[PDB]
Length: 196
Ligand SMILES: CCCCOc1cc(C(=O)O)c(O)c(I)c1-n1cccc1
Ligand SMILES: [Zn+2]
Image 1: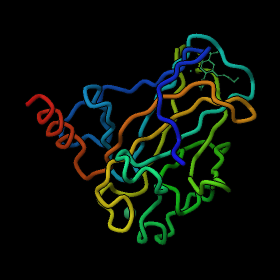
Image 2: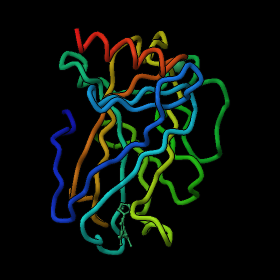
Image 3: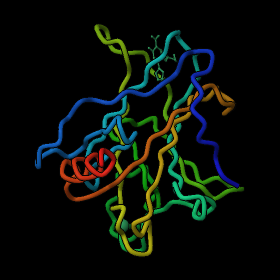
């Protein structure tokens, strides 16, 4: 099977937001609205904003999962490559096979789905800090898009789902991800290709 990627704001008006980081050579994470694509360095902080129009109930959670973007690869589980799964870079909570980690949240839970074998990471919803209008989750991607025996140059999507306490769908959004050494240059190149 394949997880749905259909954008769905749902009853709470759920959607993502991204910072405006630019495309300088030194940038470690940058989002392209024209491509709906995040470009980031390996294991660096990727701030993703969560926005709602109304407050979801206590017990609502936010889950992240990666799938391959190309249809001919969509049924294959996205996982870390044979090198990175063995490099003992554990944070003490994320299984070493998981591509996506949540940084700085001791309530993050990592799931290996017993039926689909897909990986995901889920956190409880928390209200914005006083003075803020949205909540941010900090993600890390733990392999390069190019890693041999893993993503192997195949593009991926991240699907972010807002879920109730039982895991039922409340909202969904998604974005493509490229994990690469020079996200600013790659964003500029791909946006130029799109303009041409
Ligand atoms: C108590 C559990 C539910 C609390 O979740 C939110 C509340 C508000 C609010 O304004 O009360 C909000 O703005 C956001 I963004 C979230 N939220 C959504 C996903 C992650 C956090
Ligand atoms: Zn790797």
